Image (tube, rainbow over all chains, first blue to last red; front, side, top):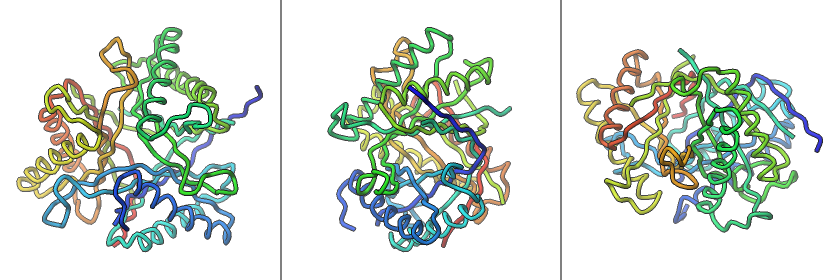
Length: 127
Length: 123
Length: 123
């Protein structure tokens, strides 16, 4: 079959959020966060034509119990995405958009704190 | 000294493999990776191990994403200087395996990223 | 504006701890990390938080990997400039904790990687 491959230097983001909502499992909290992210990314895309996709992974975050962490860690989700040159024209505008969406997710999940990191990456995209 | 890690995201193609949970799809992808990595190692003598995580990938429903995201697996590995002599050959091998996984999982698109990393290996 | 993140991959040593699910092995590793980070913080005033993910690691069955991969946990953390003053001291502390985890989990081998990152922290 025919095939295409693109390679370029770009950025990926990674966000960590709590899961706060009456979910009963990591499978259920994955679906919860997935639905919320899908809605906020869609709203942004309608304004700017920039769609910020994310891969979401179940996790627990371990920190000092004296700052409120439960024993053995707090239930969290990790969201990761990339600026794919096929869909993204301007890396600075994309980065600004990711930061905006991170703050909105923090609000929707009613979180006190939230992290968002940018990491340099070499993206190969196969079709 | 620096080296490289790779990360791939793949779908699990329920339409074709008919897994019923994230536990089952994790095992499916784990077994497929094990087989393709072994086949490649027999050809090139380069064995590419991967750490695999369950996930869901959220994109625009108008491009076919299910509500709340598509079931996916994330595969991540590294060029460990204890086992790898030539980084360029390793990178070429990872790209080969990414394409093979895309084929085996019958995926329309697939991503493979390389990230610079400083590996400490304790034995 | 740059800092460092770490990522560790560890086995869960079913031979010794006998966990029955990925949920149970996540809590096991979580509790061990919490205790070793606390003990270190009391000595050095450096607290190393981690986000822990369930996973499997796929390698050659001829080196002892189970079919479809071995149950593992991935631990990832960052040097947050709001809490961390000296990156070299932090990195040394992470290495110490990685070795201690290797000991507590009775692992033959363990990896710890450092990756450059740009951290935004929202309060």
